Length: 333
Ligand SMILES: Brc1cccc2nn[nH]c12
Ligand SMILES: [Cl-]
Ligand SMILES: [Cl-]
Image 1 (cartoon, rainbow, N blue to C red):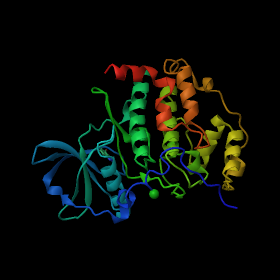
Image 2: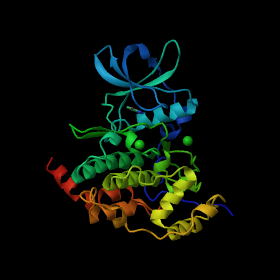
Image 3: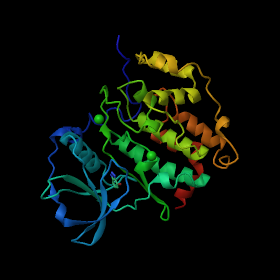
């Protein structure tokens, strides 16, 4: 018969208990402002597939970031707006300041609070042990918040984390793939960037939850403490699962597939083979050993599980011994 159903271990019913308007983004009515309140200063480098500008609010001479929404379903645009409005003011969440259309092209754009175009990817292979712990804890505050608000990010990766290293400030950005969690909803598995895709995405298990973000976070942590970018380096989406299976082992993979009665794409039958679960010590060498501790490996091991239900929640992660010194230093401000 079909795949075995799954529910989030935490924040399972939070959208059900909200008014319909909170999560029913298709029925959201946007008041569209005038892009002529803003003057674009310069294009920010965000890849071939993104149009983001530094701009000035000409009324108050404030710096902002403008994101021009490349043509895409109006439903996706409402979804990102409604999620950004719901999360506005949450810890380490980017602030949506305005929603505007070009008066001529009528192209929709999002206006955000200014952040420097310094993403985590530029910094996260040069950090101290303490700074990896510090910024991981700041990312967890954003994830525990959006999860508690019934939202999964689904595109957690270094490029989507903006850091002001001088002020030790972080923002989680690009909510364009984010969704509301509803118990029993089957989601699109064609989300996230290859190297950060959870096993649920790779084996086509659609009834996933907030725990997807916790896999992505584990991939980022592994890349940082082992200085191995990316940690799971697949040629394509099929090879991605093989790269995972060569570390996590095939026994736990086939147990996962059996537990949720997953129908494994036939292409997997040749390429997964048979692999032991590897000890993390295998990835430790003289140029990363200063970032690796028993605490870091214990924490990483609890994020990188095939079974999405087994992974730490954001709040459980924030309680791990890996963050004791960060928590203590925060309480003393
Ligand atoms: Br770049 C950038 C900056 C601020 C918010 C953003 N949301 N998506 N990309 C963003
Ligand atoms: Cl990235
Ligand atoms: Cl989607």
